Image 1 (tube, chains in turn brown, orange):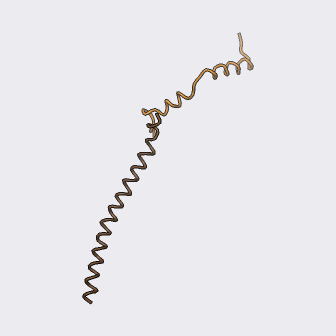
Image 2 (image 1 turned 180 degrees about the vertical axis):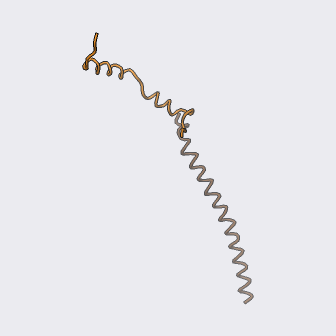
Image 3 (image 1 turned 60 degrees about the horizontal axis):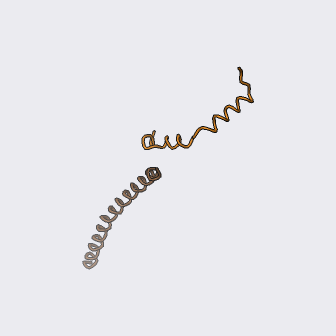
Length: 48
Length: 37
């Protein structure tokens, strides 16, 4: 009966973890586009 | 025969000493009823 009682808190916490890890993925794609922007800036400053 | 007050609170106390509220409270928290909006 105790393991059954923990269900509502455990499910919501796990759902939250899923939400956050989705946002880590979004910041990973964004951070790769940022490093690409840095390198384009790097060749442009060499071109000035 | 008739029942006056001081007999009747005694009868109520004799009824309350028997019952068991804990099993019913655990029954209303069973997996069949546990979310109910």
